[PDB]
Image (cartoon, rainbow, N blue to C red; front, side, top):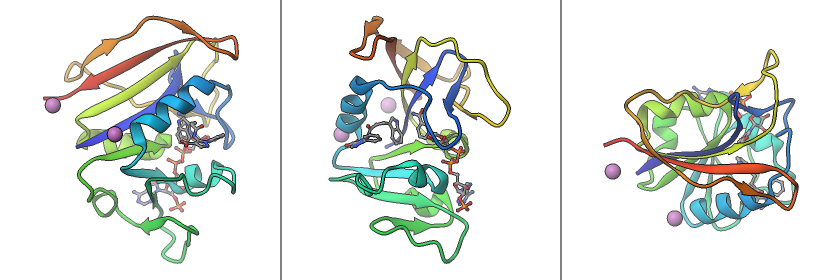
Amino acid sequence: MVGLIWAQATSGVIGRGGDIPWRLPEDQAHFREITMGHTIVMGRRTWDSLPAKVRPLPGRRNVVLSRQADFMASGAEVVGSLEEALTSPETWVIGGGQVYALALPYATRCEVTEVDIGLPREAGDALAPVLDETWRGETGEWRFSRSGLRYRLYSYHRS
Ligand SMILES: NC(=O)c1ccc[n+]([C@@H]2O[C@H](COP(=O)([O-])OP(=O)(O)OC[C@H]3O[C@@H](n4cnc5c(N)ncnc54)[C@H](OP(=O)(O)O)[C@@H]3O)[C@@H](O)[C@H]2O)c1
Ligand SMILES: O=C(CCc1c[nH]c2ccccc12)Nc1c(C(=O)O)cnn1-c1ccccc1
Ligand SMILES: [Co+2]
Ligand SMILES: [Co+2]
């Protein structure tokens, strides 16, 4: 089973200049829970946005998409096609915008957390994929973070 997990603003933005433009500690403990134990696929630019410390993410098989045939990620498997990356039964694609859009044609699940911030879509932004009518989803209640931000959780499934 192949799924995608991302945090977005209402507009669709997920990253900006190598970073996520917010701080949602509760999502860290939610993201860690859903991915812990399995394989995680990220693109190279996303693998680079992680602090050296938490690189690689403990307890998980870190897989990095890249076209650089020489690119070495200390502690992660470097492949060159997502077909190469997608080999484990339960795999979670964790970013970024380029990888999310490449993987969705092949996911049965999506774990979305939407942050309530008024964040305009600047050119060159990393965006969240778009889900059509083929996606039946469940929504949770709006919650309120130790950061001071309202957010709600979305789970989608494709039969
Ligand atoms: N929850 C969130 O809000 C969230 C989650 C994760 C990341 N982000 C943000 O997302 C942003 C970056 O995402 P991005 O979309 O700009 O870059 P990305 O998707 O993170 O990875 C981009 C890299 O993936 C590799 N790649 C792309 N297509 C490929 C293919 N078909 N085969 C092999 N390798 C391929 C390339 O690496 P080479 O150039 O090495 O080939 C490309 O440079 C950052 O700002 C990050 O913080 C946010
Ligand atoms: O906090 C998160 C989640 C943030 C996040 C949401 N979607 C993502 C997609 C790709 C990469 C990270 C995210 N992960 C973890 C962990 C963990 O998962 O165990 C440990 N440290 N960190 C961390 C701490 C500070 C800054 C960054 C990462
Ligand atoms: Co699990
Ligand atoms: Co199903």
